View 1 (tube, rainbow, N blue to C red):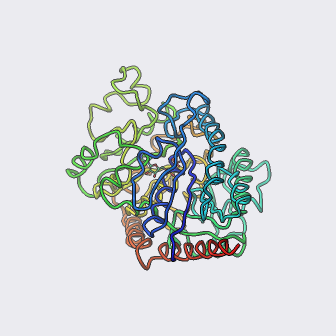
View 2: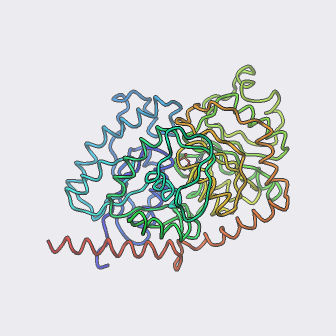
View 3: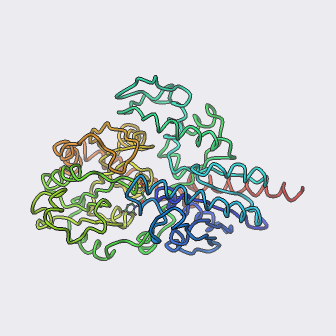
Length: 471
Ligand SMILES: O=c1ccn([C@@H]2O[C@H](COP(=O)(O)OP(=O)(O)O)[C@@H](O)[C@H]2O)c(=O)[nH]1
């Protein structure tokens, strides 16, 4: 405790991984330790400078991979071809990230599991390495259960998480490509000194801290929710990028609406639905009759579209009926989720949006797509009971318009009304959502579970640095 720790954080150029890790680094910084983000200039510009908070950037290799100069994240990409160009950009930066870490070795490296080469880098420098994937510990425990008890290569439909602390049924089997991509990364992540979890034990579950520790034989650190590090309006509004619309334009509009009368629809920064699916979503939105905030990254840069182009995905006259806001870009998700007018959150079950909704006490209408989301769906609806399910069952490989099955409008409206119409089921769902919101308000506060976990982690990291000084 005599001298602060020097911690490096290497996020992946994706909003779902970049945003939570930087807020976790901000938690270390408010303790008094010198944290350093290693990313690209555009991912660093939005980062609020805290005490002990600094960045080390290398220029994004734009023409080496063949992308426009303003594109330095997966959220700016609209194509699977563009997604791999981000990956090759990470491969090119690896050379300079390794040289910088070797020249100025830190007390501890915290890197995303999509960068598994950090294992050798931390090993040859003999410094403790932490892993981060943005998942829930529940989801990590479930995916490690399938990796030990695999599905037969003819499986289809629902399946049970094998030999699990609770009996839970996922509504679709993972694609073969997901297993062959996740399995190598999880194996290297388990070689680390510990896993950082952007969550808190009251939400994941103690029975899964003890599952991960005793069955899998590894350490996980519940430091979340990290978004709670942002307290001001400007801190909650400036996340990832600048919001496309004036933050005051959202607040003024929402301030006129009733409490729990607006539905927020957003499917993350990696999911783009085809025009036919957006048409069903919009048709279900107007048939529900509720005011809405709909995030449509599929149409960013497509304003003042021709009527022929807008009728590909919107019912005729949808925009003339001004019962909501179409955000064709980046919306202040923390600002909108925290407003009392928002009563439901139609989500893709990405983990950042999940813990953000938990902190805001907004029940969720679940629509998983890929990755950890199908596991996250049942953590929201069955285990914790803070949402309803649309009923989707297509686990896609690519969320860049890879959906082959159409989710009907009646299916969506039925799910929207189950929370917004204020039924008995919806009333007690919101009561279970506020119960977690009150718990979440102090988990990273002094005395909270996530706070004391960060204290124990920093001590053990300080211990290992003291041993390296001996040698
Ligand atoms: O218009 C948008 C879309 C997303 N987000 C943020 O981006 C993250 C989305 O990550 P998540 O894990 O929920 O989904 P992913 O994009 O990784 O699939 C969350 O922090 C959201 O608050 C945002 O601020 N504005």
